[PDB]
Length: 401
Ligand SMILES: CCCCCCCCCCCCO[C@@H]1O[C@H](CO)[C@@H](O[C@H]2O[C@H](CO)[C@@H](O)[C@H](O)[C@H]2O)[C@H](O)[C@H]1O
Ligand SMILES: Nc1ccnc(=O)[nH]1
Ligand code: NA
Image 1 (cartoon, protein in one colour):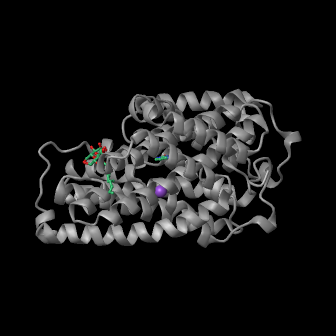
Image 2 (cartoon, protein in one colour; image 1 turned 60 degrees about the horizontal axis):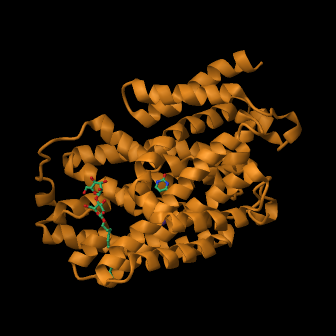
Image 3 (tube, protein in one colour; image 1 turned 120 degrees about the vertical axis):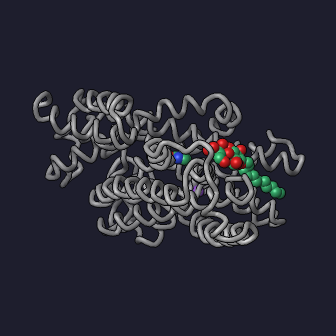
């Protein structure tokens, strides 16, 4: 397997911070973060917005730097990392939930491209799905190299064309002064808002090691996560709020259409989805490879076929389902981190032989974290991450050995 799905990335295949910075910005530069940014924008004061977006994405940035640090220290995908805490076969459970929801998001994302475009152009929505997902599936066959190519192309155009569009929109609106006078008629609960920020990428963010395992230097992995999730996801949130405030449209590609920038709009839509969806498919192949021992390349292509032929169905009904399953993903992150923090020395080698088949305490910890998210007050994802990590740190030394 060229994606090294079954063991540590060897020294000659490692990559530098530049490629991994763009790959990860390619993940967060995504329309759904713009949409959520418009919700936060219309439901919060100008100060509350930047406080919620900055606090939330910094929490995201710290959570993902840990995972990226561990991914890079070891050269292991999230799924191989999970073998330490969940067991060799126990990890199939996180791997399927993480991988499956990403196949979900991929199909969703194919529809997010083909639907606006076929409406704007009259072209058959079905035909566009076929062509979009097929193109996106072919590129994932070529692995971390393809993700590097797409995002070093996509990310500059999105940041720069998108930023210019934000500038126009605040200018034509009366400038910053007008923007900071807009008032929500029904302000959003601040803690709900934090959950929406963190919740925009905690699922893909829990698979950070699948990409930054390629980094030679663990400290650089921390920089990648912060640049991508603190700075990058914030920028996407600002795009969405600016578009909501100036025009009632939270996707910057709707703003550009409003401004007569039709070609920038379609290009920015296609580039932001293609990068996020390729990451999704890539990580899902790694995840299903941990389960089946098959080539992650082959599985990624299979995942893209299924995701394409089911795109609309996933866009419609299965989004509430995709959000539901995903509630088990944050605790899985806290367990992995906590197990590394507790048992660093264990991670010195990738040694199948000292590993468990299944650690029931890991599964028990995930359930507890889910309960902590559903009951405890505060920020649901943070409570759900800390639920799994704290209860694992308590019960694993006791009930495992
Ligand atoms: C040849 C040119 C073709 C280019 C056509 C492509 C441009 C289309 C851009 C995306 C298509 C529509 O995108 C649409 O944006 C609105 C923003 O109000 C999103 O709405 C979103 O923002 C609101 C707040 O505004 C949030 O409460 C919520 O998270 C979400 O529903 C819609 O969920 C999405 O359907
Ligand atoms: N593929 C994804 C899109 C949006 N958010 C995620 O967490 N993952
Ligand atoms: Na993207």
